[PDB]
Length: 49
Image (cartoon, rainbow, N blue to C red):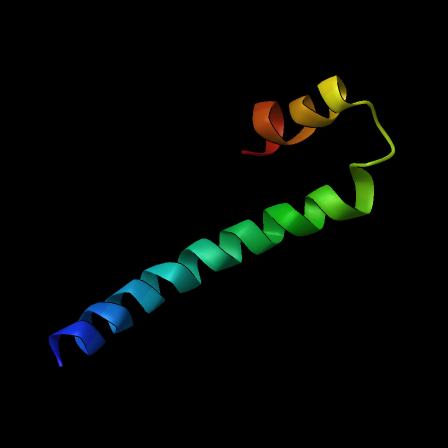
């Protein structure tokens, strides 16, 4: 029961994290890949994150 309660709390935290990461991933897919590896890093880590 304790493990299940911990899993449920983890799942709510996971849902918030998942929505944020999913938005970041969609932004990365559509656009990133057309650029060079040095620039590709700057698009998400320097501006989006």
